[PDB]
Image: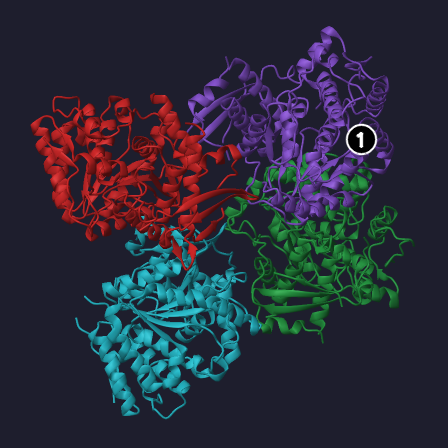
Chain colours: A cyan, B red, C green, D purple
Amino acid sequence: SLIIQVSPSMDLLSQLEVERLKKTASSDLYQLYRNCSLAVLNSTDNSKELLDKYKNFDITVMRRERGIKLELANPPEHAFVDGQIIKGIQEHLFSVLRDIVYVNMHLNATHITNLVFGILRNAGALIPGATPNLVVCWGGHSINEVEYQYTREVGHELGLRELNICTGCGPGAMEGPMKGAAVGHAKQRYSEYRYLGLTEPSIIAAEPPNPIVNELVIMPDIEKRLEAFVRMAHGIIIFPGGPGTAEELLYILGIMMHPENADQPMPIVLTGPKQSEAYFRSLDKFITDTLGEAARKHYSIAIDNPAEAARIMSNAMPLVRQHRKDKEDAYSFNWSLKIEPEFQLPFEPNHESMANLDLHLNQRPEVLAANLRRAFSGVVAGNVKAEGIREIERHGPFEMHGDPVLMKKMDQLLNDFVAQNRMKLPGSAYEPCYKIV
Amino acid sequence: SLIIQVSPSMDLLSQLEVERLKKSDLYQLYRNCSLAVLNSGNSKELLDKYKNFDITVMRRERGIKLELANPPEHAFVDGQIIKGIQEHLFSVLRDIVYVNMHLNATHITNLVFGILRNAGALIPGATPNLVVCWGGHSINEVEYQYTREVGHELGLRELNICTGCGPGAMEGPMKGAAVGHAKQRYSEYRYLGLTEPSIIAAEPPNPIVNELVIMPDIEKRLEAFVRMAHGIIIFPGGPGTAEELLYILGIMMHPENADQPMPIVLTGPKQSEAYFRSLDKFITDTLGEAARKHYSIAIDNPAEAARIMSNAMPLVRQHRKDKEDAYSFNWSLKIEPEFQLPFEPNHESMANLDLHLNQRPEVLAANLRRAFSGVVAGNVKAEGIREIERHGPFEMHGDPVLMKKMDQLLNDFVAQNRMKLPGGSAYEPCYKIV
Amino acid sequence: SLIIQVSPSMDLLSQLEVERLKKTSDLYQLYRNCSLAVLNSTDNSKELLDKYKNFDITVMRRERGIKLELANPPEHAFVDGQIIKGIQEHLFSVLRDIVYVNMHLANATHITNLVFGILRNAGALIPGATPNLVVCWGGHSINEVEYQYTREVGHELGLRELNICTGCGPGAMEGPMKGAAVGHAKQRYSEYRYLGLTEPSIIAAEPPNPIVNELVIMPDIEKRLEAFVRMAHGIIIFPGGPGTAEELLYILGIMMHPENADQPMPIVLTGPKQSEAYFRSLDKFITDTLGEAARKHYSIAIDNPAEAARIMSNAMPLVRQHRKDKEDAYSFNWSLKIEPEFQLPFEPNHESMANLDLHLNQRPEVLAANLRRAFSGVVAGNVKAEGIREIERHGPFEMHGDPVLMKKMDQLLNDFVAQNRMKLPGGSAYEPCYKIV
Amino acid sequence: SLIIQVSPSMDLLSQLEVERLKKTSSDLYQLYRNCSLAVLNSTDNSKELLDKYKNFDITVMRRERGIKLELANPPEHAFVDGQIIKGIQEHLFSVLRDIVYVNMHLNATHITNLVFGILRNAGALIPGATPNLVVCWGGHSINEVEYQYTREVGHELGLRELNICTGCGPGAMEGPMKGAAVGHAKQRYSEYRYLGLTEPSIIAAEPPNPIVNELVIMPDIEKRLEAFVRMAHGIIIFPGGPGTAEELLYILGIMMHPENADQPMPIVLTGPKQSEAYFRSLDKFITDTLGEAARKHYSIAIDNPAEAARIMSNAMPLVRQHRKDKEDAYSFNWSLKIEPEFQLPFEPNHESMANLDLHLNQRPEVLAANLRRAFSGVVAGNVKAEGIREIERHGPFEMHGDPVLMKKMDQLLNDFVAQNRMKLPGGSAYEPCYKIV
């Protein structure tokens, strides 16, 4: 077979740290690490049937004289420019290894936040000396040219303002802002730029990191990745997207409506091009019809104005600075943010647990947000997660019930995603993994 | 007034160096060059727009401070001058000072060398990786997207970019390369922009240019290009790009340059095939079939253009050592004084151009170069535009076979919108072919 | 109190890592004492502490990480009212290492991996660095001729682009580094590393000079010993007292093990002309007790600084290739065999010093291991607070064994007393913490 | 010949810049060769140092990465284990850089502007840097106690983040930089600057130590002197011979200009305890010749290295405010008034020494400027090759004047002789190059 060697950015490892990543009987670790490493070599589509395409891929970790070398059997050939692996992709492979190893060397509420902290610290993601300048960007993996161009323009304007970018991984509004920021930073001579990509193992093949990401972090699960986003964020920019972006929006809004979070200054701007006005009218209406009028104080909307969204982020930075100091908190990690256990407790989407969601309009707005967060994660899981497609493939779409006022508003929004092509990367038509009862 | 202080890269200057820049001809050139870099975003009626602008060089405790009176407001993001634009201001000041503190063939080349070395543009220990990118300032979106794609592909191969200044193909590649370099983790990227005082207002440097150099004239800029180049990529363009093409092919056809390995790739999107078929034909119709060994054409393949440059870099390395030459400056390349002698285009000197097909191909190249620079001057240079206001178009004559071909090519530039950036009135020719 | 604030290399810390270091806490007292030792960079007792009873240190987790509030710090840590920047760095190194050890008390394999873990966490193990680390060993209490000699050897190491790993304190612990500061400056070696390894029970007796740019605090004497020999690419030993003899018997015992026969690392004993009779007596000590087979592991180089350094320098490619052959790291010698008689933590007290097997019918490695322990007791009785307390209320440590081994040891200990190697010379004469039966 | 190649910090050069230092332009090569030889020779203080290395030559080669130098039979003490000390390598390119600049750029304003231009080309004038440069003057030939003192002051300057500008050579020219290497390392001052200024006629007598990281070759003595005082933010003067007296008389003659009365730069004369009588005598010589008015411009500090360094350090904010007040550079003191008598190059032969006006009925600034030239001639007659050649065939330089002055100068020179300051002790005994009438 074809064998490539990869040389190292990264620490020495012990035999203890590394023996767990041998192909072995009655452990799942190697295949987790292999799949994550495979995904990184594949920056095509959004299904996890790419594991069927590269079934003869394998990876070996070697402890040698200058640290770790990796040997790749049959890697995807589009990792390669002129027979050599793009240096960014090389670095992602070591980020994979670093984070898988950390987490497995380190197997309630304080415990979870502390683990999220530890992972991020081990990754080098929390820079002690840094002034607040980190903007989390959220938006669709499946987006048209006009929306993509708009994300690039916003990225550009953040770049000019010496701001850094944290996103998820994948195509669309996950790579657009970094590409624009590449230009904006170079205009502004900002050499210390950071493009942070946060992923987890069940999502990573579906949405592989761009090699422009210069700090990849693999979180253990979706909820810990979401906690990482909101604890590192200094501002939040939200683009148009499908159910993944909705999940992320409802996560932060459930958090922000807590009374303890009322002096948390973190700006959220929903932003899009002129043609996303109808998307944003519909989305704003959904939020206020479900979570109440109270939610609207936590965000603002900017249509057709990249510089404004980025100006808002930029202007808010001294606010974030002052507030961290008032709380005796760190700049780089928001300890003082109150996240309730209903946002922290891992949700494994199957038919049973999708049914058992209390999606009724007589809850606390926070707990309802926590529930719809879970709802939208199940939609994601049924679409893109290899385990989650299997449960649809044997037992049909996930069954979902509640207040019919909410249920019909949810179904309209979900169908909007289908109609605007937000569910899937386009190339046959989408069939729901969901069923609203 | 609106008064901005800019602090500094920039060396200390003496009183002797500074005194000459006090607000006769030297202040104006310096002011106008500095106005140009503040106005990033193709005529020189941009002087009228900011008539109340002034600049003061102050010698202070840590070096040079600059005071701007009424600078253009699009240099500013949120009340602060873009840092790249600040660096351009000091690059302007560096180069005006150097040229004025110093000022045949060996004299001219050593001046060109000295300017570049003073600018820090000649990095002694660097391996060959510099691609010169030529192309139109006035190009469509498909052509523009193509330039940024090639730039991307050059970034991924760890190659650097030298270009002229301005919009269009002058900014595209750099912007693609920003992404490509970032993916490739290439932190030591170099985006060289070369300009001269007579064109800088019409074609201002993008703030993404991180090495701006100002040459004293067009001919010394063209020499700077070809002595620094390790390869050349040429996109579709107008008369300025044609000038540069004919400059290089003229040079490359000299027998003493037969061992010069420098690759030249003419490249463009699918839709540019007719452009290149027509341009390639013009080239072999004028210079001969002997011209074709000095370039190739790569249509609709950005990776191929960049692979050709990348593959050539060890060959450039070996050739420079074979000649006992520098990596960063090609001293060994032969430039005859017909390519070096500064051409001042006016009504008189345009009509006195010798443009006949009964000529040595290198002399015809050097003469066609002057013709196309003439067109450029009448379109973009303030003194050129003023001369067409006063006297009408530059007249050109010669072999009527050559005259028909030139006219067709010029007419192609007009019809493909290559003469003039959109949004004014229609282009009217600054040339008339007799 | 005189509050001096020390501003923040040093990572963000959680509250959980930090809370045990409040004044109530045996951990705080340890942290305080290490921090004060570091602030007190001209005697070798730990009634050093009793000069500074009103000293305390508060850790504050703030916006850019840890700040330190010092209450009444030693005033020779200051130059014109500002704390020396090297001492500031040492304060954070202390914090880092005490935190790391305390967060990791969860068995030969456990010892080595902890030592690996501490060093890697400290930044002491550089991936990608080729072998250039010389461990320098010698007495803390030496004369000017001996001192200038270590400084000359230091200069010769520096010219050859070699780095220095040593213990902390005065005398031969600072000499080499001061010499190498000149040597490295001539050679333009800006990436110089001067490593100082210590542990909490000895740090107050032998405080790190500010010139040490990589201070590491190991949890005990034995783990410092392992760190020395796992990191060393060469070893230079100057004349010294019981501490230097302990270290010498540590390494000779390791290197005589038959599994360690291929290990290429040089050991050079070296001193000025006047130290010939010191080495004549110590070479005789070693060969009478351990064997003629001990002698093949070290050489002796009197009065040639450039030759000691040259032996180190010429050994580097040999050490380089050997590590490659073993698929071993350059920076950490995993393959070296350290048997558990060199790892087992020895708490010197009256009972344990009595139980030592010093009989000349042993395996020569195990005799080396017991002589190691014997010499650590002498050190502990002299300069360590808890060993001083044992000596105060029970009298001197009592050792027995083969009567002409014991007469050779009594002679060698008496040489140390005569040469003022036991203790930096105070008003009263040295009284032995040891009696040989 | 043994050919050693030196690879290229330093620019590309043209054929035109290089052609002139081909061996045949004929004068220029021999000057360039001698400067490069001196640099490789970092033993004694004659200029029969060129007679030992008659087969040495140097060839400049324009190559692919800039300049390569081919050394034919270089001195072996430029080498450590068969490789040239990188400090010395950098020194060869400094020589080349400066020889080229001066000879490509061939009254009062033009001399200052060339001094400036040389310094700026060398990289010696740093934009953005605040005042921290201490000029150190002192003997080339000094005992161990005076040497150790200079190292201690150097250390104390180092601890205060001050940089050092000095002459080249042994003695008080190397002492401070070696102490500072340690003091800068304690304070983590990695951006340390050790400037050594020299000129072609003195370089072989007094070669740079490889510890000097910024070597500048000036075209003559007077231009070196101007470079010192224009860059200085403070001045320390140790005991020394005629060359240090020369520099003392330079600075004191400058500082007694009424236009210089506001210049805040401190001058501290400093020495070990045993040099008290030396300073007693020199203080008397200065106040007798120049007046009580000379004494307000310096102080004497005996046996306190820290106080000498403290005076320098505390004066920096005063120097800073003053350069702001005169709208002058931090790095280069344009505003300092230097009269042409201090600028005008003196060439010591027998006629110019005899034509010196040396009469105690003078303007103190005129008398200082003349005594400057007198001492320069003693230095030239001692160490300069063309100076020694004048006395080898016409006998000692003759000086005459006010017989009170002439006996004071006689006594001071005889003190230099008695204290071994004229010549490094261990050749033949010193025979005076001067006769006082």
Tell me: residue D119, above or below residue D184: above
The disc labelled 1 sits on which kind of residue? Answer: Asn
Left or right placement of residue C5 versus residue A320 in this view: right
Residue A94 location (% of width, % of height) = 43, 58
For the point 66% across and 16% down, the residue is: D347
Q: Nearer the viewer, residue C162 or B171?
A: B171
Q: Nearer the viewer, residue C381 or D175?
A: D175
Left or right placement of residue B21 versus residue B431 in this view: right
* Res. B9 visible in picture: no
Q: In which quarter of the image is residue C236?
A: top right
Residue A6 location (% of width, % of height) = 40, 52
> Which quadrant is home to the N terminus of chain C?
bottom right
Tell me: residue C418, above or below residue B373: below
* Res. A324 visible in picture: yes
Q: Name the residue under label 1.
A: D143
Left or right placement of residue C152 versus residue B276 in this view: right
> Which quadrant is home to the C terminus of chain C?
bottom right
Residue C41 location (% of width, % of height) = 75, 54
For the point 41% across and 76% down, the residue is: A223
